Image (cartoon, rainbow, N blue to C red; front, side, top):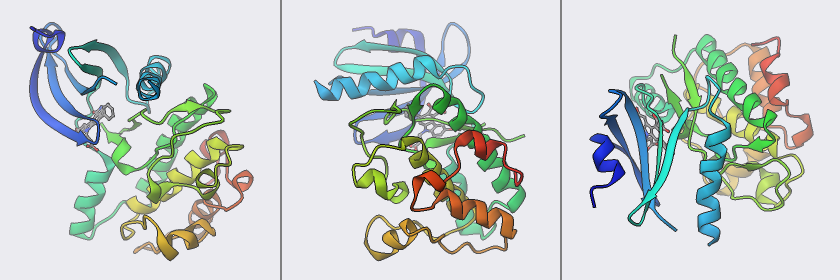
Length: 256
Ligand SMILES: O=C(O)CCn1c2ccc(O)cc2c2c3c(c(-c4ccccc4)cc21)C(=O)NC3=O
């Protein structure tokens, strides 16, 4: 062996685990910097999916609100991607700590989260790409800076086949195999991500609560928000994708 991975990096800790691969905090020996490196089993259609993640990274390396890519390589029976390390952890971890402490993101902080990820979405979408798995565990924290990561579901905007993202954040039209307005699926997921940050109960994976949200009804939020902000969230989850704002329209919105 003596892996590129082994030879170029000192592995500090495991930071993430999944159905296909783990993420490690590593120090690159030569440059002294810390990176996040995902190491997954080399896969085929599964390989086409794994490569799209690499291709998406290699074109989305220039935005402040998208995790930067450095390198990808294959060795042994594993594929590796070396990304920017965000030292603030995931949004999902911040939200889970807030949950236990009963102190959530305040309206000002929710607006900042919405605007920052909204700018990341505007960049991705400007590249004729959609993310398709926006949720708190795929937003990373680094002024706080929020950065979209996990490009495992990224596809071109006019794709006729799509890999469906997390059920809790999934827009109905996507579940229905209607891919005419893919960018608005990202918008819908961003609104529910902001709801979670606002202190909501864990979102439903299926059943009747799941359908009511998809009717355009915001889950309960345990804090008072301006009507104008609540109304922006509600329109981002409109059952008609064309009524949801585009990312460009979101980032220029008077509420933000
Ligand atoms: O398990 C999770 O949801 C997060 C794992 N994870 C963490 C945990 C704590 C951190 O401080 C950063 C990260 C982290 C990072 C990334 C990932 C990641 C997700 C998908 C593919 C490749 C890396 C997971 C990733 C990344 O690209 N930059 C990152 O900083």
